[PDB]
Amino acid sequence: LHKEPATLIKAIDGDTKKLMYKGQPMTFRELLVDTPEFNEKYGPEASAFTKKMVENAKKIEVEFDKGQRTDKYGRGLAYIYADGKMVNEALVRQGLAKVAYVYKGNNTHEQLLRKAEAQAKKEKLNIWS
Ligand SMILES: Cc1cn([C@H]2C[C@H](OP(=O)(O)O)[C@@H](COP(=O)(O)O)O2)c(=O)[nH]c1=O
Ligand SMILES: [Ca+2]
Image: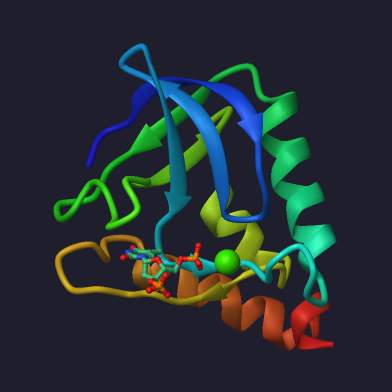
């Protein structure tokens, strides 16, 4: 896998955001995670977490996996990095997302995120409290 440039257009919620990629606006959906919706428990905190992480970043990068790059809704499916730090992983590590939607062909960072979830679950953080 490799990292590609992108710029933040706008935070949306825990696991989606509007980025400019190859000069075009797209909604990105984070691979391998599920944040609660804004109206659910920990939803506002997920959105806040993701929003801060991507808004404070100097450099946003996207990393596609080996499989499908866009979902049925036209959302790009990628791993998102903010100053080299994976948003998908940080959400999981803090208990603000669950590992989810693990499809074959698009699961390179699965075990990395599962390790992060275990740690969150041990620490009883947020969703696991
Ligand atoms: C994360 C991800 C979601 N999706 C689709 C499956 C789900 O379909 P349904 O809309 O039919 O439930 C939906 C979940 O996204 P959200 O969690 O953003 O709603 O997005 C994929 O197709 N591939 C993926 O990698
Ligand atoms: Ca969600």
